[PDB]
Image: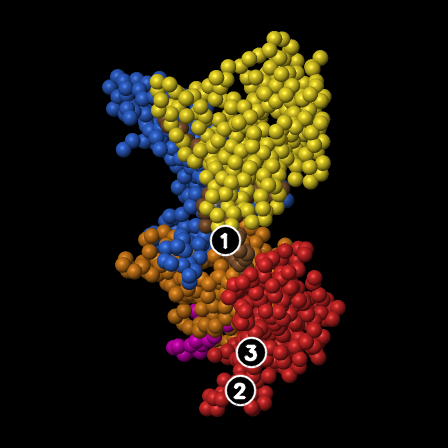
Chain colours: A orange, B red, C yellow, D brown, E blue
Amino acid sequence: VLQLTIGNSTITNSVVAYGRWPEFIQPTEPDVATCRFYTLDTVMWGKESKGWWWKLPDALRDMGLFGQNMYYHYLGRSGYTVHVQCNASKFHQGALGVFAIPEYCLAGDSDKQRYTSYANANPGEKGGKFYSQFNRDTAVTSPKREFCPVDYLLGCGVLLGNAFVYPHQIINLRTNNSATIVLPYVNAMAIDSMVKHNNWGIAILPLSPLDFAQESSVEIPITVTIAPMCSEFNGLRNVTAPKFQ
Amino acid sequence: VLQLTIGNSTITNSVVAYGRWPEFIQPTEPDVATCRFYTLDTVMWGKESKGWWWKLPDALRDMGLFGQNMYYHYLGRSGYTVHVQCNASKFHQGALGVFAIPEYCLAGDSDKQRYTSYANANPGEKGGKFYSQFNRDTAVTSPKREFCPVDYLLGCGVLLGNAFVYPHQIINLRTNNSATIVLPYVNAMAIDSMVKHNNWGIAILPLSPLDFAQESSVEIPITVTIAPMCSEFNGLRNVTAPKFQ
Amino acid sequence: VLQLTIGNSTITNSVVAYGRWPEFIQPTEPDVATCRFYTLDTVMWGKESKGWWWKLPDALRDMGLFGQNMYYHYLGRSGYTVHVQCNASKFHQGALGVFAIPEYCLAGDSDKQRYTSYANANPGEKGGKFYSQFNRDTAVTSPKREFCPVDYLLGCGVLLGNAFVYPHQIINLRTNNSATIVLPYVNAMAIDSMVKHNNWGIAILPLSPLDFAQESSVEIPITVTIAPMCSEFNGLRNVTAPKFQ
Amino acid sequence: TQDSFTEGGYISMFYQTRIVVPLSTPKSMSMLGFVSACNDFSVRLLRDTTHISQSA
Amino acid sequence: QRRSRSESTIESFFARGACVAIIEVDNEEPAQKLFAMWRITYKDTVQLRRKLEFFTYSRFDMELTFVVTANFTNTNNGHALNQVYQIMYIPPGAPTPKSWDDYTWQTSSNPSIFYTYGAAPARISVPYVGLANAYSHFYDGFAKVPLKTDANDQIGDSLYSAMTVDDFGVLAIRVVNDHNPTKVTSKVRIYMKPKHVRVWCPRPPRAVPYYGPGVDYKDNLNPLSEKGLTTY
Ligand SMILES: CCCCCCCCCCCCC/C=C/[C@H](O)[C@H](N)CO
């Protein structure tokens, strides 16, 4: 609706998660190097798309100096401002539910429990995608150790309809083309490791299927832009180099 | 003499160059990520060593988050605290002149003027070494385009004896084993690019040859530790990746 | 560091055990006959020395009038000032841990428990010596009934490294050549028999082995001088004559 | 107890320059290490130590 | 407004004691269960687990109540005298029993309850013993990160959503009495009651059967039943 300027990045309803604005608690605080909007890779919303999911701060691990501070320091905390952009014409119809889940633990694909690997559990800016059904992994010799989120189960054994208990925003193409959620730092500790722990999960679900006129196939872009807010790090040491394979 | 604590690094006369302490002038200022002592690779002072030279901030280009901020931002400024360590026994004799030259331009090795390449002019933490005489480059087909510093000419056409006009410290093994120079930011501009311009040059010359008892060959280590002070950067953009070859 | 004058004996950091100075509680108090430094027999610290131990007041049982008062009276109390002297050159290296253990009970050498004899448990000014390993007594016919202290076990089943919980002083030849510990009277009673009960144990352990230049065998003297302080006796009767054999 | 979630960090030691000794001096020396807690230190949830055991 | 919400409060919502574990302890001639070690958690049962997982973070003081029920096993006329059960709490790091008469049962510093059979169920209270500022029902992360310099992948391999292997220790339950000539089998049921409960970040309730200590789902993934669109 109005100008949204952070650092050196400006974006032309916005919901504050849990009514709490990001806030600070000698932590290293880059007021400019990290407090800015980083744009994730655009995804394509089609008529056969089940959904998308990203993990924060994992999605910003390779975003400018924020990732460098995240890997160099031991433990850091950061709020976020997520902005989802999806522009469509008056003749397009659809709705996206954008949910910011605290501790968005997801279910695996194998009978073995909690067997998902770090590489698969931390996809980065590409994120992942939900599925209509639960596909059980059958590669016993070389298990994929990847999540198997289910659209209507939200990937966590709960019903999608109740996901609105989480902070949420609905992009309904007939009325609005963008959503904005301001997430504070949510954790059981005032500050925690970012490389191993993800504080937030952004799930975008097509509540209503996309459609345009009488066209058989229609696809429109969705772009996610995340701004770290009041991010502070502590425990400076040699750089961490996670094995992503 | 006394404890020297900066950030998370502590070192157990110290001269302030030009009697000016490093000082600040929305620049990005990492108060902890950059304000700390980084130790350069140790060199070996022998009886046939002519000298060593490093360029600042080039020597700290790959030192933690200071290098990341240097490459990510457009223009930055930083003071320095250089600490040279060389421990020897009571029976060792020698003296090192440590000079902090502003704009320490060096002479080339070819008849072509100002033909030194960026890769050779920016050695990094390894630095370079002076030479007794001037060796003219003869590889016309593939010129080396490297400096040819001369010990008694200081590598700049001036006499070594007058180099004491610069900020300096003498490590005389009989009285002291370490030297400490505090350099403010010196430039014609309040802030300038660090990737292309080096503000300081640290030259260590063996004023008196090293000797120990009646031993024919003696070598002792020299370790340089540099702490950026009041370093602030501006002009954040994609990361710079210089071609060092 | 400074003059240390007691009675008619003067010695040219000093630690007060438990921060308590020796103090008095009609006890017989010789202010001069007993309050003076008595020098024990010098021992020789070599490269194959495991340690030494003495028991107080047993070590002063034959030292001037202090021993006479100790044997004549029934029960007496006395603080001590222990001064260990070990002078070495700049080219000697080593370290001695001098520990004042309250109730320094030691382990025996036989399978029989608490079978150590009074004669062996009270060596006098000569003291005893620790051993690298535990040598089990095998003379069933004539058991020696002597202690078998172990250097790393401190002779009491505890680790040597934790012995610093006791009052201690480190004679490091590179920095200091003497140690001084001031022990108050420590016991479960305000005054107790001295002939049967030893209040303190002085253990000197070579924390770092002695070495000198490249010499194969080097030995230097260690001299212990103990000054009774605020010693008072009570229960005068005929003289006690312990059987030392 | 050993736990990667409450891991505390690492302690390392390196030669900054070297050990330099003259002639007629031992070229090999020994260093000792001591550990202590600061005034901010605190412990919680008393338990039984695993160091001492008794044959039953 | 005269109708109140006193019973919908978080404290009232958890003010009931929920069974979290059933432990079998047998006394017989000494492959055997003379002592049973049970790891402390509410995830062995679904009801209290589901109630707690209504939220993401919690902080509560716990109250444990032990109900012991003993029975004979194929006794003809062999009988037993009243038994005493020892329930010893072993926090992480403390030694664990290897037998029913091990030295660890001395309980020099490990708290223990000696319960006499036929008496009231044994009740004690525990404060908030969390390392962090609140309990984490859901942990979107690992405890180890696999690094490029790791020699093998197993160094950094860790279970997803697992914080610590030994969360809060175990309870070791034995029968202090020596073996009677006839076997006696007892079941100890542990009932956990949160108190002074505080919760944060509400979550939707579980809709499908639990499968393990995590959010994993395996079967019965079709909860909703058939119903007409326009049928009342
Ligand atoms: C004989 C005395 C018994 C003493 C019992 C002490 C056990 C201590 C356990 C306290 C907490 C256990 C249950 C609460 C923690 C929850 O599982 C958290 N959500 C952890 O994820």
| Residue C153 coordinates in the image, percent (x, y) | 46, 34
In the rendered view, does B138 fall on the left or right side of C181? left
Give the alpha-carbon distance from disc 2 to disc 1, as whole Å.
Answer: 44 Å
Provide the chain ID for the residue under circle 2: B
- For the stretch drawn in magenta, what is the main secondary structure? strand
Q: Residue at x 31, y 20 (%)?
A: E180
Task: Look at the picture and state if B65 lies above or below E216.
Answer: below
Query: Cβ–Cβ below 8 Å for labels 1 and 3?
Result: no
Q: Which residues are magenta?
A: A209-227
Badge 3 or badge 2: first in the primary sequence: 3
Pick the quarter of the image with the C terminus of chain A: bottom left
Task: Look at the picture and state if B191 lies above or below A73.
Answer: below
Question: Residue tagged by mark 2?
Answer: B136
Question: What's the mark number on residue B131?
Answer: 3
Between circles 1 and 3, the one closer to the viewer is: 1
Quadrant hosting residue A53: bottom left
Q: Residue furthest right?
A: B19
Question: Which amino acid, by three-letter code, is at mark 3?
Answer: Tyr
| Residue B150 coordinates in the image, percent (x, y) | 59, 80
Respond yes or no on whether mark 2 lies under 8 Å from ligand 1.
Answer: no
Question: What's the mark number on residue D27?
Answer: 1
Q: Do the residues at pointers 2 and 1 share their chain? A: no
Mark 2 nearby-residue class (10 Å; few <14, some 14–19, many ≥20): few
Q: Is residue B244 found inside the magenta-colored segment of the image?
A: no
Question: Which amino acid, by three-letter code, is at mark 1?
Answer: Lys
Task: Look at the picture and state if B151 lies above or below A241.
Answer: below
Q: Is residue A217 found inside the magenta-colored segment of the image?
A: yes
